[PDB]
Each structure stands twice: as structure tokens, then as C-alpha cells.
Amino acid sequence: GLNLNTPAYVKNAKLIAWVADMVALCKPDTVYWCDGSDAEYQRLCQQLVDAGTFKKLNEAKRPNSYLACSDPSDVARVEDRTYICSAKEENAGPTNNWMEPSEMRATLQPLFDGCMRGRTMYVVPFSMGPLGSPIAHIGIELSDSPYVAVNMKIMTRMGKAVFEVLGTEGDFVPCVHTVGAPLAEGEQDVTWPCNKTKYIVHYPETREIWSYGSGYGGNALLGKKCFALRIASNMGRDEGWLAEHMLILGVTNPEGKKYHVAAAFPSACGKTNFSMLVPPAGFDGWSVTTIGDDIAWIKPAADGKLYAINPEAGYFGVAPGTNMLTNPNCMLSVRGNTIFTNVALTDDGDVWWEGMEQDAPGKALPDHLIDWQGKDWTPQIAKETGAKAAHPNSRFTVAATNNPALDSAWDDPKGVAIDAFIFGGRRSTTVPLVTEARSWVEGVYMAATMGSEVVRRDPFAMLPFMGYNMSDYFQHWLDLGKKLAASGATLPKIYTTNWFRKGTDGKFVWPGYGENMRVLAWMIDRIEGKGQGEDHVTGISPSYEDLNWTGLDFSADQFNTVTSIDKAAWLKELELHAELFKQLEHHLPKELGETKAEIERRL
Ligand SMILES: [Mn+2]
């Protein structure tokens, strides 16, 4: 313990032994255990400023906020370098990259050997989920990136409080991360260390996560995707719960009754926008509050209800496109205490990203910016070269509590009971504005066949994040629905939504954003037994008179444009579904084929 600079409050022999093994391998100059305190956060931020990784933003424009820009090779998750190394290839499935675990371990051994020379190893303890929640789990991330440490502080419950939960023998998800850039004696560092060679590896049987070469987002903040979705989905398959790529919101109606919805979108900002939706005119008595905007851990309880927690403590959101029109709650969240990554820098020390011009007088672009590559940027350079000031995948990192619409139960260890699931997508035709599934199986089918416009399929929005065979995951969901039904409780309703039906002129007809409240309210009306609708091939959809249009000029003709179901359109759709089910043929539940046949027979 002393050889690792181990704090006296760490009483977990298995943890210390593992850290010792990883220290012997990675050979850091020093070891620092993060306590998660505000003072530590401030010290690390100043160190990032001194290193040039952070620029501190103008305190008058964005208090206690920082801007980091990354190496152009290291700007996003690299799915081609992400591996599920289950013992058997079939347990990775056709949606994951696989390698024999022994071969990958022998591949990573020489990369991690001495990877942290000349650097500090940060021991980052964290809880995914409220501390001590029965739905929460602990991870430890070893990282040589102080950027990882400060972002993990915001994104997780991080620090010394974790060891109270862990105790002397509690288990944890072991995570090891290196930027893959050992420093020699006298060698000068760079502002964004990284390696052109990257590996993001998961060993499900042992819950291990190994990440080499990237300092960025989902590759390096190992709680968010690697733990919260890939490892956790395996744990949930074994222990009877779900780890989903879903926002969680609470919605209260004028009577005061509160419902909770979990929703998966294939979009970059769809969940964040929907999860912080501000009710438009005509809904003065409604409230929408955010439990989470990205990850949901959902555990059935004895009462036949599904209880979801958000396992994260902050938002790691895509910045471009965010403004007061599309997402004012998000804009308000990032007014301060935020870490921005790869957005642009203004001449007065503020940040900017494509889309903020919607809030500016005359919708005017700034005259000059420093773009995420450190290059001069002007509207003329953009207009003539297409250069973006902010990277398309640029991010804000901010505490959940900065969101003014944060739900008061966001940190409740019991979670919230899910009344409905929503599965979205982008479809110019075919898919109506909103459809309610007639049965659990038909809802799983909707989730399994989610697509975005050619139409790319993203079942459950989990295509990059499934921890095991996607088909077995389908079966997990079906088996869950059987158990819930057997409790006699009311099942969560399952909806499909599509904000992006196009007209004859090729333009979107549904205004979206806040107006999506009119669709969400129909779901609540349905849950309460007051909502009406007509039945069609794929499910039940509202008629024009079943939605509240107060405060929105939207005609029955426009409504028909975004809700019309065409026999020929869906005949083509099912052909696309068949191709998907061919890729996922292994262990594909028969209920999916039976559901497709029923849609065919009904057509
Ligand atoms: Mn996500």
C-alpha cells in the first residue's frame, strides 16, 4: 500500500493488489489517488491550464470554465478500435469487434508496459449511480490523463466517498487507461497526448476495461460508455436488469400526477433536447424534468415496476446545434462551471459553436474565432473552405445540478418507475409521428428495427454499445417483458416516434423541439386511460383531434403528412427489416419473425 501512495482510508486489499499490478506494468513516475474534492478539482484544472491543455475562459463571460482542444486524430470514439473480448466470439455477436481474449491480452501487454513513464497515474474511484444505491456499481479508473480525472469528477460520483461503499472486500469494475505517450527524460510534452494506435477493450467475464491511445470522450472517460453500457449490459443480462442508451425524464400534468419516460434516439442531441424539453404554449400546467440524458440502468422490482437510475452525475453533451431555440435548459447549464472540448474561442475569451448564431442579433456569425485546431476562423474562411469553428463532435462537460430542470429525484438511490419507453429515429417517410405498440413484443420489435435516414439500423440505439450478442439482448428484453407481465402490474407502454417526416418539398413538417410536448402529452394521456387513437398496421396512433394544438398553428393536412401510413411504403420497410434480421440471425428470437409476419399478413 505505501509503495502505491495508498491513502489510509483505502482498506480493500484486492483493490490495492490490482493497483500494484497495474503500477508495476504501466510504471508511472508518481501515483495520485483522487479524493474528488473541490480543491483537488481546482488544482488539476490549474495544472491543465499550465500545461496548455486548458485555456481558462473569461470569468465574466463563463465563470470557472475551461476550453480544451484535442489532437485532430483524437476527436471521437473509434468504433473500429473497440473490442468485446468475450471467451467465445458468438458472445460478442455481429455488432461487435472480437478477438480471442488471450490474443488481445498479449497484444496489449507490450503497449501498457511502461506506458506511463514520465507521467502521473491518477487513481479515479467512482460510483455509477447514487452512492450506495442497490442499482449502483463502483469502478476504479487508472489514467495518466488529468483531463480524464477532472472530467470524471463531473461525470461520476468520484472520490474518497467511494471507499466507504466499497469497504474491505467490495468488488469494482477495473478500468485502466493510458494516452499511450510515455515521456523520456527531458522530453517535452504536448497539449493533448495521444497515440495513433488505439485500443478500447472490454473483457466481459472479468468486467475489465482497457483503453490505450485516446484521451477523448467515450474512449477515455471509461464510466460513460465502456462501463455504463458495454460492461453493464453484461452485468444486467446476468443479474436481471437493463443498461440502456436512454434518457430518463419526469413529466407532471396539471393534476399533479408524475410519470417517468425513458427514451432512446439514434441522434447526437435528440436525447438531450427531449430530456430537457420546455413545454410550449398550451401546456402551462405541465412540467418536464431531467433524470438523465444518456444512460439508464433499469431494474425490475417486486411490484412489477421498472425502476431506472441515471448512473452518471453530469452531462457530456454534443455542443454544436445547442442554442436557446433548440435547448434553453442546456444553454443555461453551460453558463458556468463547464469544461468545453473542441469548440471555438472568441476574441473576448468566451466559447462559440455552430448554431449559437441563432441567438445573436441578425443571426450574425462572429467576425473572428480561434477554431478547435487553433486556426484563425472567419465567416469567409467558413464560406469558402467549409471549415467548422467547433468540431462536429465537440462537447460540454457540466454537473447535472447546473440544469435548471434537473429532477429532484435525479440522485435518489431507488430510481424512478418507468411508465413508457420511447424509441425514436429519423425517417423521411414510412414511420408516423408517434405509434404506441399494442404489446410488449411489438414494442421490442419497434426497438429492434430503429433506423435513421440510406436508412441505417441502430437497434435500441445500442449498435456501438452492446456488451454481448445483440440477438441475446433482444431475448433479454422479451424475457423481461414476460416477467413484468407475470407480476400483474401494468406494463410500461412502448412508443415509436419520428420527428422528421418530410413533405413533397423535401422540408421537415413537424416543428419538433418544444412542440414534441404535444406528443409526450398524448403518451401520458394514454397511460392515464384518457388518450384516444386509431389502430393501424404497426400500432395505435393519435388522430388529429387527440392532440392538444393550443398555441401551435398546425393543420390537419400537415398532421396527415407526418402520420399517413402507406401500404407500399411499409412493404419496402419490412424488406429492410428482413435484411437486418439476417445479419442478426444467430439466436434471433422467433417473436421478431412472428411479429414481422403479422405485419405482413395485416398488410
Ligand atoms: Mn450517448
Image: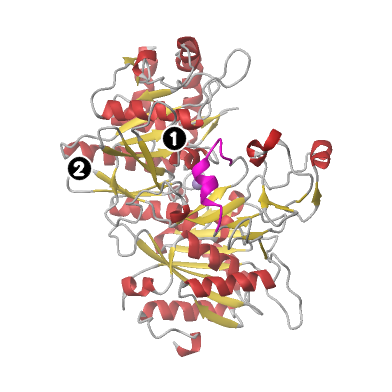
**Quick one: SS at disc 2?**
loop
The residue lying at 32 percent from left, 15 percent from top is: 535
Quickly name the residue at label 1.
Answer: 585
**Snapshot quadrant of residue 380:** top right
**Snapshot quadrant of residue 35:** bottom left
Three-letter amino acid code of the residue under disc 2? Gly
Residue 331: image tag: none
Image location of residue 505, percent across then percent down: 63, 14
Q: Does residue 181 appear in this view?
A: no
- Vertical side of 207 occupied by 377: above or below: above
Query: Taking 507 as reference, is 547 left or right?
Result: left
Quadrant for the C terminus in the image: top left
Q: Give the range drawn in magenta.
A: 323-336
Quadrant for the N terminus in the image: bottom left
Q: How much space separates mark 2 and mark 1, taking CA atoms?
A: 31 Å
Three-letter amino acid code of the residue under disc 1? Glu
Query: Taking 602 as reference, is 328 left or right?
Result: right
Q: Does residue 397 appear in this view?
A: yes
- Vertical side of 394 occupied by 265: above or below: above
Q: Nearer the viewer, mark 2 or mark 1?
A: 2
Q: How crowded is mark 1: few (under 14 residues within 10 Å), some or many (20 or more)?
A: some
Asked if marks 2 and 1 touch (Cβ < 8 Å), the reply is no
Q: Which residue is at the front of the view, 521 or 541?
A: 521
Q: Residues within 10 Å of mark 2 (few under 14, many from 20)?
A: some
- Vertical side of 265 occupied by 78: above or below: below
Image location of residue 7, percent across then percent down: 43, 84
Residue 324 sits inside the magenta stretch:
yes
Image location of residue 205, percent across then percent down: 40, 60
Quickly name the residue at label 2.
Answer: 304
Residue 147 sits inside the magenta stretch:
no
Query: Taking 377 as reference, is 603 left or right?
Result: left
Image location of residue 23, percent across then percent down: 53, 80
